[PDB]
Length: 341
Ligand code: NI
Image (cartoon, rainbow, N blue to C red; front, side):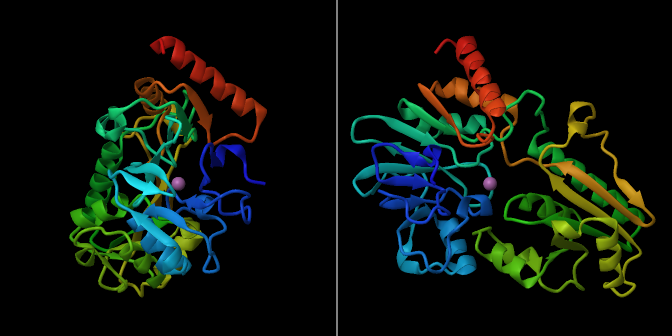
């Protein structure tokens, strides 16, 4: 049944709770972003109201075929009323259209649900600053000290330099970038740009990207593989057999592949620096796994919480084992003691 950490007390609301059938007492279903663990269960046959961002609404309409009459998109940074309750949607710095949700309960309690987020100091100057938050529903994906990773800007720098060098040395080298959901678009767009190319992709993927309100997007992507020297593939195909297969399909236009797998975390981060990353190579094919994260590092998460000083924290990730739960509750206690709230 629907777990308690997906229910917002004092309202008829649930968040990201689309795979439990009809939730007893739910009058509005919020969707934080268009990733499958979160939208799981939505479909063209859904007949309850869905509240979400404009971009997430484009994707529900065009990709899931949810009927328009049930999609209620809201603008960001704007006080809105939903079934009698004031709410605000904030940018979650996750994938395109991802939001956090502020709920202002009738009784005076204020709740922040983060959705999936990558905490950032810039959040400390949104409408969050303007009042106290009593309860926090927190994306705890990387809530452990071993999870360090570099900034997004450092990772992109590394990829840009790597690709530019390889292709300048060998003009017949193809670059391939793996994808399986929205998010991490900067990886392939930044590379394409330094190489003066468009990104070539399948029709389904091109459609997906046309939902995202990315400016000048028509200048940046295409369905014509032949005209483009950065290709996107399913993440499943980013391996030697899969890439060898694809090279055969390009008809002798290229003789080398450089490929990128944007990973979350990988234990090489406990020792090695970004400057010091190396690929896996077989023949004329090389694969880089790069730690481009759209979730908070441990330190980013800790800083956010210590700034916010909530009265209660409810984890939404890693909640399935007692050992995880217990480990997370200890870190929360340390943070609260260290900061004094
Ligand atoms: Ni996500």
